[PDB]
Image (cartoon, coloured by chain):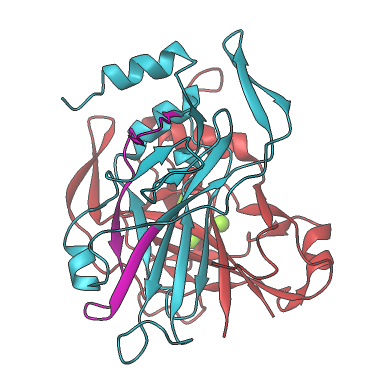
Chain colours: A cyan, B red
Amino acid sequence: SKSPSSPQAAFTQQGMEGIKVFLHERELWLKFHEVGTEMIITKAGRRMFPSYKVKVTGLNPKTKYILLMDIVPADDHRYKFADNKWSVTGKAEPAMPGRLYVHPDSPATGAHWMRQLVSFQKLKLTNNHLDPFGHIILNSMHKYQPRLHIVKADENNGFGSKNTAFCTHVFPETAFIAVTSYQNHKITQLKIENNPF
Amino acid sequence: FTQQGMEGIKVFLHERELWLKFHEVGTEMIITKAGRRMFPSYKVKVTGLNPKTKYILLMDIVPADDHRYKFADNKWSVTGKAEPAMPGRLYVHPDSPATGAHWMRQLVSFQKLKLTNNHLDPFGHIILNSMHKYQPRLHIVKANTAFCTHVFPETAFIAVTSYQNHKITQLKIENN
Ligand SMILES: [Mg+2]
Ligand SMILES: [Mg+2]
Ligand SMILES: [Mg+2]
């Protein structure tokens, strides 16, 4: 497994700088990344595989935090897959402001979040731009970067103030191309032989 | 989630192939009481800055996990749990505070940074514990404060009091 040519990046407001995030099963992610990761989108919605899970440290144990995820474009291109290669075949079709996925345990104390793995498996991806279930909407054959966001409560431990602050974190190895069906046989194979079932 | 004049910023790791080779073996960095420079040295090209407003460039070195490591039978392994994972000290780049175009004109070198194993060091060197894995981090602050941070995972390393791997100590030129 190569490492991604892009550094991990993070944007952090004061009060968040002690926090650290660790990608669960990073090597597994590196293998898909190496090949070029694809995620299937349907009208009903598909969960991601591999699923995005993180261990968090450095949270204030009884400050309240909101954990959420969004999936933003990584570039402005359409792609096609021919001759076992991804090529740029034109300009990305600008779309929705990205929806959020909020972790269902939010709001919660740092103690709660640090106690185990924050998992986002339940997050679903659709191609339907009229989705009525608040699923994340994506464009087939476009590249996307998942982002972690952590929101901290204020002194009264309650959001709605301007004394809230956030971490934003990006693992490059979790980037992927959305697809209505798999293109690279290696992706299709990695998923069958890593299928946790 | 509006990052300020900062979504455009990109960072590029210098002499990266060397970091990759060394990362593939398992990067080791010797720490001493007087303090050792990092090898490989840490240098980056910075792009996408507001051409000239004042920025401050920092580096910290933080735990990449919580394990203690042993090196046995030509291999690293987990062996226990580390001591403290922060609060730590920083290296503030000497050119700081300075301007975007300035920062962008020549490679930003962190070569003067040193690593010591003396918990009572008076020279501002970064204090590490041997046989613990660490992760160099780059922090950028535009002069209510906010950090853009860049982490190159291939610069992670285990801190040692002397080189361990025979692939380093018995360096084979036409091999690895
Ligand atoms: Mg010495
Ligand atoms: Mg030296
Ligand atoms: Mg020595």
Task: Give x and y (percent) for residue A77.
Answer: 69, 34
Give B86 or B7, whichever is nearer the viewer.
B7
Answer whether residue B38 is magenta in the image. Answer: no
Can residue A1 be seen from the camera position used here? Answer: no
**Residue at (47% x, 54% y) in the render:** A99
**Residue at (66% x, 29% y) in the render:** A78
Tell me where residue B2 sits by quadrant. bottom right
Give B97 or A191, whichever is nearer the viewer.
A191
Task: Give x and y (percent) for residue A184.
Answer: 48, 15
Can residue A115 be seen from the camera position used here? Answer: yes
Answer whether residue A56 is magenta in the image. Answer: yes
Tell me where residue B24 sits by quadrant. top left
Task: Give x and y (percent) for residue A156.
Answer: 31, 92
Vertical placement of residue A119 versus B71, above or below:
below
**Residue at (70% x, 69% y) in the render:** B5
Start-end of magenta stretch: A39-68
**Residue at (29% x, 45% y) in the render:** A24
Question: Horizontally, is A186 left or right of A111 in the view?
Answer: right
- Could you tell me which quadrant the N terminus of chain B lies in? bottom right
Give A149 or B15, whichever is nearer the viewer.
A149
Residue at the extreme top of the image, as rendered = A83
Question: Horizontally, is B145 left or right of A16 in the view?
Answer: right
